[PDB]
Picture 1 (cartoon, one colour):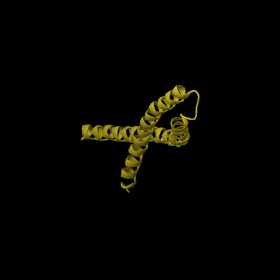
Picture 2 (picture 1 turned 135 degrees about the vertical axis):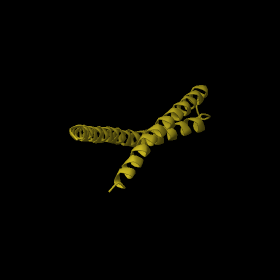
Picture 3 (picture 1 turned 120 degrees about the vertical axis):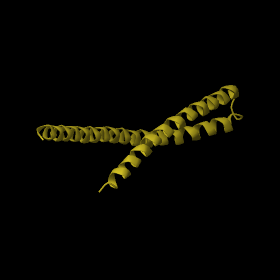
Picture 4 (picture 1 turned 180 degrees about the vertical axis):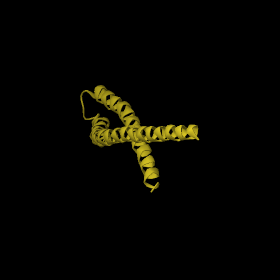
Length: 109
């Protein structure tokens, strides 16, 4: 009886602490998704600009005296655009994961 009462109060302390940690962790993940959204919007513009640049370099490389170097620079841009793309995919998964838990939470009530 007296033990049961202490058990209940302990379980309530556990409940409260768990709810607070779940909530703090959700807010932390929200802050990371918000940061991913901004970084991704900025990477998408860099990608577009750089992709166009790289495409022009490789195309026009023949009207250039420094042909070898224009072909080289275009190739280096392509490599870097592959990495940029990889980074954007990760940002997208961070955002996607957050939207998924956000939706699961909204369905709780």
